[PDB]
Length: 229
Image 1 (cartoon, rainbow, N blue to C red):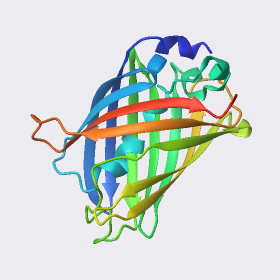
Image 2: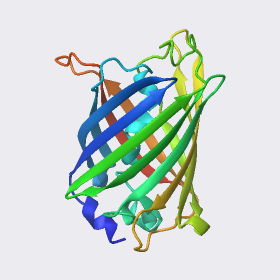
Image 3: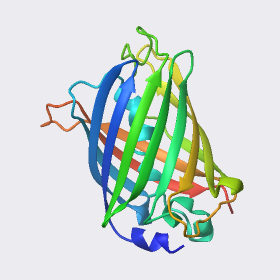
């Protein structure tokens, strides 16, 4: 597509999130870069309101949803890249993240170019969380397992849908499932690529900046599109 030409090099990324989980209000700011040619994303997130009331791993898919734009689509699959085709005008995203035996996050995001920078503005609303649950009780390990994002076309809405499962590791050795349902529609009136069924193979690594005293998260992600031969 035409929008793919904007991703041939290193693109700066800005992430801004406003959240409310069970009345606990917070804000997160993120800075980094993505290099789609290698399906690479590097981002550092900082909680600007103080301490994050939810564990950092629970916010990775939301805070770094722009990784979908940096997915390396193999040459034979390039006509299936919705994300880049929606650029520079961008897309609006909505998700419902359901934590098994706990609450849910409902998100609304806009991913678009502001000059040569890819900006992701997000609003997160979390309800029905248990006080001593895995989320509000901070019982999740600071790590991330590899996963696949299953994409299907939504022809009538001129966009896409996505479904995936995240398995957060609990400190006792168990797993906290987070079911994701996603919908994306373009902001602009220009033509976008409506894909055939495929998936985004994701690999993530969470770390800390040794010199950072604020509540933060450093993320390194690698994403490759697959599913079509």
